[PDB]
Amino acid sequence: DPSILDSLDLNEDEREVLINNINRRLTPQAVKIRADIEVACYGYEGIDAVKEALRAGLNCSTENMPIKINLIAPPRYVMTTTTLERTEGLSVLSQAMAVIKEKIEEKRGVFNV
Amino acid sequence: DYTYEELLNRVFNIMR
Amino acid sequence: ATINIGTIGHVAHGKSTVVKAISGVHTVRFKNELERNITIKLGYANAKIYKLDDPSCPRPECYRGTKGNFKLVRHVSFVDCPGHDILMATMLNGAAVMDAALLLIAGNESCPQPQTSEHLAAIEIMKLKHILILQNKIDLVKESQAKEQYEQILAFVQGTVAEGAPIIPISAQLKYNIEVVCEYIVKKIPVPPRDFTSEPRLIVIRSFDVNKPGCEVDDLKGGVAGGSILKGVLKVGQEIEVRPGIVSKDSEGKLMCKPIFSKIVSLFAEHNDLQYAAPGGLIGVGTKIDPTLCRADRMVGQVLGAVGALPEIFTELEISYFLLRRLLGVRTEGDKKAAKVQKLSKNEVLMVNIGSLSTGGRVSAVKADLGKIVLTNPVCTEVGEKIALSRRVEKHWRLIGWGQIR
């Protein structure tokens, strides 16, 4: 983050510190969170909406970057969130509640927190 | 039932 | 997928060699804690039935008995029966709208054989007409037992219809006479008539699941089940309605029954999937919908219709019935002549195999020949000529009654 790193470079730049020491102890802190989903829908607007549930899986795969949805819980799956940024949280919340606030009610389905 | 005597000769004379 | 022949298996045959002689090998099957093996179920085959200008019907290599350039046209099918004498009553559920029957006789057990016509005891109401005489003792005790035993088994054929195809004395471990057995089940067993251009239907029997962990969310997923056709031939990609489907809970009206249809992809056919559903066997139906509803184990016992179908489905039931005046076939002289079959009591569990779906039977009012019942879940209307009432009399089930929709 100070990539202007000059003014007594000791060495070439920081030699013994930057071989492992500067790099060696970043000490990043993060806490695992696992915000869930439960969407489904039924009907023939529900067949359109179960196509739209599968593309909702596609949609929280590719649009707003929730990453690596796995298939371990056979009724309903998970979407991941890990702090390297922490500002993925409000974006994921805004989009999941935009899903519940405009997406599902136009297609007459069931979903909550 | 001729099939039975067919067995009785050939099957049991050659195989179990 | 061509023939739903039945089989009646009592104790201690050696069953994988005879069934795999007439079905090839076992399917890859899965998801343990299944359903109890005295309930409704179906068979399958990984083979086909054909000939090679030959009594022998081998497995699909074209030379090894000799040549004969096999007809890759159809595939044989089958209906399961494991080798214990318990396999009576669910088979008699299955002995109504199947195609034919095997008939299994051993010599390992009692030679004045008790179980076979103890097993085969609906030769009047439903269909039981195409059988074979099949001795399973060439192994332990030789020609004296078989000598008296052919008189034993021809003492069966008189009014009890036990003469559909004569004796085959084998042990299927040798796989012997399967050239002759296959010649019998090609020629001496016919194929009954069907309908073709009828609007197709299905009641769901054996559900599955195809979303084991480890894939992506962009996969095509859905609800795969099992079934077999009663009418029509079912193509791919149309309005495939399931009429109540889910139990419509807190349903306050009549038009509050939900319009739910689907599409279809997989129709498993041993090597392929012919998208027009080939009847006469287990069909591998897989639905388009991606719910928690059908692709779980939640769905057994619902219809396959179309938009604007005929049956309206509610609970208003009244049935006309009668009974069986002993436990059917069982008569053991060592203190078993009081296996009593008691009249329909009020509020008693049953099994009402209306058509080919197992729902437990509850009852509400008892007359001598008719009864007003209410049932454990909403159940479609299939047929009035048979309502196969079964009832607890022992550790497992036995069938007790015959019914009529009123």
Image (tube, coloured by chain):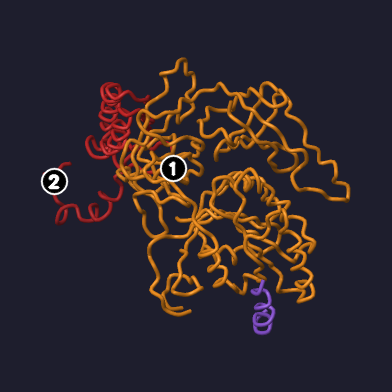
Q: Nearer the viewer, mark 1 or mark 2?
A: 1
Amino acid type for the residue under numbered disc 2: Leu
- Residue C83 x %, y %: 66, 58
Residue named by callout 2? A5
In the picture, the disc for residue C231 is 1
Q: Is residue C211 visible?
A: no
Above or below, C120 relative to C342: below
- Residue C233 x %, y %: 38, 46
Chain letter, disc 1 residue: C
Q: Looking at the image, which residue is at 59% across and 67% down? A: C17
User: Which chain is displayed in red in the rendered image?
Assistant: A
User: Which chain is displayed in orange in the rendered image?
Assistant: C
Crowdedness of circle 2 by 10 Å Cα count: few (<14), some, many (20+)? few
In terms of image quadrants, where is residue C170?
bottom right
Above or below, A19 relative to C308: below
Q: Looking at the image, which residue is at 31% across and 47% down? A: A25
Specify the quadrant that holds the C terminus of chain C.
Answer: top right
Query: Distance from label 1 to label 2 (Cα)?
Result: 81 Å
Q: Looking at the image, which residue is at 46% across and 35% down? A: C303
Crowdedness of circle 1 by 10 Å Cα count: few (<14), some, many (20+)? some
Chain letter, disc 2 residue: A
In the image, taking residue C300 as reference, residue C324 lies left or right, namely: right
Q: Looking at the image, which residue is at 45% across and 31% down? A: C245
Q: Please name the color used to draw chain B.
A: purple
